[PDB]
Image (cartoon, rainbow over all chains, first blue to last red; front, side, top):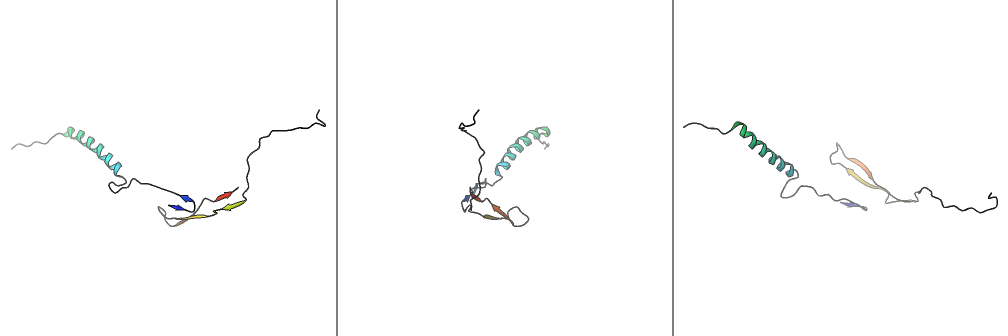
Length: 50
Length: 49
């Protein structure tokens, strides 16, 4: 935006391919996967006879 | 000792200015985003000192 000799330009993280918070979400997933895979080892797999 | 002598000096003084004209005097914005209501803000003046 340019008015009367003062101008400003901004480029957001928003894009057609990815949303503005997509970086935070994708890092949250990276942590949750590690966090969840490790915790499953505390409980272990499920077994039932047949 | 210097009753009828001349004297000369190299001197340092503070910078000073006066406003001799106000130029592009007012610039305005109705800022509304992330406000309870429309607000009027005066953007910077340019001064010819």
